[PDB]
Amino acid sequence: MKKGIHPENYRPVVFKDMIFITRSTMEAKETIEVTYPLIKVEISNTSHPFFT
Amino acid sequence: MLQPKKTKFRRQQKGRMKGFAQRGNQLSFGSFGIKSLQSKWITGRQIEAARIAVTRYMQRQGQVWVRIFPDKPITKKGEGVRMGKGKGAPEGFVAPITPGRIIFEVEGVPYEIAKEALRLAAQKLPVTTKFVVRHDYDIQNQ
Amino acid sequence: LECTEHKESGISRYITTKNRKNTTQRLELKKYNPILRRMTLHKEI
Amino acid sequence: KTFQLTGTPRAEFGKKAAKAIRKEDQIPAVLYGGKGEGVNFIVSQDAVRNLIYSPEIFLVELTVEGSGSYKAILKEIQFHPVTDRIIHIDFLQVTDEKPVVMEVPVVLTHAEGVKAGGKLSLEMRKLKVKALYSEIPEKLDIDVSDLQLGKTIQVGELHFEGLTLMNAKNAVVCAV
Amino acid sequence: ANLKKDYQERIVPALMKQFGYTSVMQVPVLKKIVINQGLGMATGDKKIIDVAVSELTAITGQKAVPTVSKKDISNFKLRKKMPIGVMVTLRREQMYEFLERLVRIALPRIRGIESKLDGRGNYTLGINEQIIFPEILGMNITFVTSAQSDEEGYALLKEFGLPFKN
Amino acid sequence: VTKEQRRQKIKARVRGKISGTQEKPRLTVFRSNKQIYAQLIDDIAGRTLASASSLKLGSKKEIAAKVGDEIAKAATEAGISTVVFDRNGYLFHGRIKELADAARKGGLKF
Amino acid sequence: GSSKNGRESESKRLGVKVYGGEMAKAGNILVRQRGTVHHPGENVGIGKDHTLYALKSGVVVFTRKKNDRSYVSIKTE
RNA sequence: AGGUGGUUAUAACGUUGGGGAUCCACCUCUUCCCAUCCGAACAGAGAAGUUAAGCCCAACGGUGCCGAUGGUACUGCGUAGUGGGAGAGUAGGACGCCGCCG
RNA sequence: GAGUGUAAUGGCACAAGGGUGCUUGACUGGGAGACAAACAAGUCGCACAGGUAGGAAACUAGAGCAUAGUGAUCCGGUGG
RNA sequence: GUUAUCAUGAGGUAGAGCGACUGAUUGGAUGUCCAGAUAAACUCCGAAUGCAUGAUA
Ligand SMILES: [Mg+2]
Ligand SMILES: [Mg+2]
Ligand SMILES: [Mg+2]
Ligand SMILES: [Mg+2]
Ligand SMILES: [Mg+2]
Ligand code: NA
Ligand code: NA
Ligand code: NA
Ligand code: NA
């Protein structure tokens, strides 16, 4: 909350499972139709065997 | 020999025994014991000799309690040493006792054996003593 | 390593101590100048 | 279970009065409990000789002359350090209103099996019990016909009557 | 605000149904997610304390601080001045967004999770690899709940989506 | 540790030097979530000399002015000036400052 | 044969100087103490070495309070 | 059901129940006064919600606290007398008592 | 049951223990009255005038939680 | 000035105690508990005397 110290780039982005926008720092080089910031990931919790 | 595992101080001022014992004048563990009629310092060597004597009697059936522990350091100067120049060479520990304090407690043996076993122990001690039986004792069940 | 100090600037002087290996810069404190009857800066000599 | 005691009135108090009392082979004594103040009176060494010097316990039926008649139990005996003679007694008044803690003898009444060899050992000689004064046994019998090997009967693992075993539960009342 | 709606709109209306509270203030609510890691190796090589700060900030999104020692133990070369820990205390929505970054992507990237709490209802997690997250020498994770026993804590815990076990 | 043990700790620190006599009575304030109160107290006597509050009377800081002024009129009639202001475990800020400022701006040397 | 002892320092003559009931002039020393064995009450001040002294003339009063804490104060008129 | 004092806990701590007219509180959000790694604390802005918790009331001898009478220890004077009289423990007491303001 | 640079003892919760913001009162002229006391020495403390620091203010500040860390006179040095 | 009486005050000795601290310590059941017990440099307690102040004789 303090001005300054907090690092920037913390902007919303939707992760891909291989879609849910979540405020995260990691800004992968991509875009998508706003909610442009996108990151591609491997099997999420929807595809992990034991987790499902 | 009975002595503290460690002490805070190496020397101690020789105190003063004043009156009758107000603690440890009653039997708690056994049914028979011996109690002092004088005030005196009791040494560890005296206690070990008396305990071996009472344990030698009663064969191997019964339990003996020592109800005093020597925690008072004493010293002695020695021959050819004049007065002054500080305290002398250490000489072990003693336990100060006053009249009424119980020394040896015995249980597990009939009345006559206990009376005789503590008589042998009292004859190794520097103070005259007295036999005590607990007031709830039963002469018709031993 | 704690020596006498004399802060200056009749003249106005204040005597005090300080550790010469801990405080290595000359002392400079505001004190009351009796001659001027107001606070002025006194520096070590 | 019952003892007959009587005692004379006591008026003076202090170092001088008490020393003169025992000069006649008497004992100062007090009685207190529940409603009302205490009672100061005098008993004799002959009178209380069989009340205290005994393996038994009794409910003292006390008749203090000049004051009245009550029921009491032994609470505290004061002994001389050297002579081991009685110098003071206080009796707790007992009524049928609330329980009272007292310790009754416990007797190991045959031994279990062949037994481990002359053991049959009574360890805890007395057990604290709280109950109405007219519910306290004269004795605490136990039957011992099980576990002739290394065993122990605890204080908690026993139920006698409408008593209450306050005698430091999870302890050991017999063994071997 | 990803699991925030899922909790207030959906998860809360079920906790009261089962445990049967007479109100809505008796239901457990995790209040913070504390993260920490021990840097005893930094007692002899302290250049790896700043790097931990930089890594411990890209994950949660909010700056962390060093933790100074508190004891004088020679067996760890420890005197009561050294920085040997880095902690971050996420709270309110900051832990809400962080929680979704973990239940979906952290446990999935594991090479599930133990079921044992402190007894007051605070599940703590020590993961031995820091690359389990996207932005990245493990780090502790503690969810301090408003529950009372493990029963109430577990119901709040499993509703979020924590993989847990059995 | 529970929003009150600290306040009582701060209360006793302030009371270590601030009290009230027949002259210079103590000005005491209590801040609730919705209201605000004031009281003039004579510690030697133990009784309250005057009072004001906003229970029966803008944002919360805008209402502390009226409490800070209504306590002046009550003390103005009774003949009180040069009161001493105690924090009562409250930081000197916000609503509490406006109450103190209004009391000073009136007839009291708070 | 020797002693490693034989040392001592001068005693400081500490303690209560004006007892409860007596009259004090302003400035009078009431208690010399190490620490606040006694605490300053009304009209009583404390020095650098915890010396208790009278700020006003009057009657010396001792008073025990919570946790058996002792206070010294002067009763004026 | 609040604020603020006096009385050295017989006043404290705790346990089990009750309480939402209005109050106290938790509660909601950080644009502003102000604050920490974090509106957790502190501060500001509100009344959408609850008595669940703090808080207050009833009952409880549970932990602590108070505590006789008698006897004893010790002791001033004096050479057994003449005066003072503990500590511990036991009967018991105690779930406060009083002022001001709203 | 910790800490309080340093022995021991006494003290400390409104902390005298731990943090930060600003500061130099580790002030000029002072000593009503006491403690202690062979002397020489030692200790605590004013009232108010001048000018400051912190504070919203009340107020506090003539060094440090206290008690050791020391050396007369003669004779010389330095600044007014 | 002294002594007595009354009023007021501050004590930490004798004694006592040890789940009130520190150190030491006995036996049991088994760090937990039940008993037993110690000290110039231990104290949750605590006299008798003595001491200070005022008044009267
Ligand atoms: Mg000395
Ligand atoms: Mg008496
Ligand atoms: Mg003078
Ligand atoms: Mg003694
Ligand atoms: Mg003793
Ligand atoms: Na000497
Ligand atoms: Na006598
Ligand atoms: Na007593
Ligand atoms: Na002990």
Image (cartoon, coloured by chain):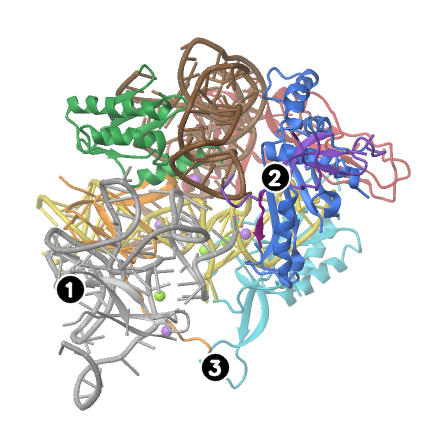
Chain colours: A purple, B cyan, D red, E blue, F green, G orange, H brown, J yellow
Q: Position of residue E91 (x, y in %)?
A: 58, 35
Q: Are marks 3 and 2 in contact (CB under 8 Å)?
A: no
In the image, is residue B19 part of the stretch drawn in magenta? no
User: Foreground mark, 1 or 3?
Assistant: 1
Q: Is residue F28 above or below residue H99?
A: below
Q: In the rendered image, is residue B111 in sight? A: no
Q: Report the amino acid beneath label 3.
A: Ser
Q: Quadrant of residue G16?
A: bottom left
User: Label for residue C42?
Assistant: none
User: Label for residue C34?
Assistant: 1
Q: Report the amino acid beneath label 2.
A: Tyr
- Mark 3 CB near ligand 6 (8 Å cut): no
Front position in the image: F48 or H71: F48
> How would you rate the neighbour count of disc 2 (Cα within 10 Å): few for under 14, some for 14-19, many for 20 or more?
some
Q: Quadrant of ligand 1?
A: bottom left
The residue that label 2 is drawn on is A10
SS of the residue under disc 1: loop
Q: Position of residue A11 (x, y in %)?
A: 62, 36
Task: Please name the residue shown 37% across and 23% down the image.
Answer: F59
The residue that label 3 is drawn on is G2
Front position in the image: A30 or F109: A30
> How would you rate the neighbour count of disc 1 (Cα within 10 Å): few for under 14, some for 14-19, many for 20 or more?
few
In the image, is residue E67 part of the stretch drawn in magenta? yes
What span is colored magenta in the figure? E61-68
Q: Quadrant of residue D52?
A: top right
Q: Quadrant of the C terminus of chain E?
A: top right
Q: Is residue F22 above or below residue J12?
A: above
> How would you rate the neighbour count of disc 3 (Cα within 10 Å): few for under 14, some for 14-19, many for 20 or more?
few
SS of the residue under disc 3: loop
Q: Report the amino acid beneath label 1.
A: Pro
Left or right: D46 with respect to A24?
left
- Mark 2 CB near ligand 9 (8 Å cut): no
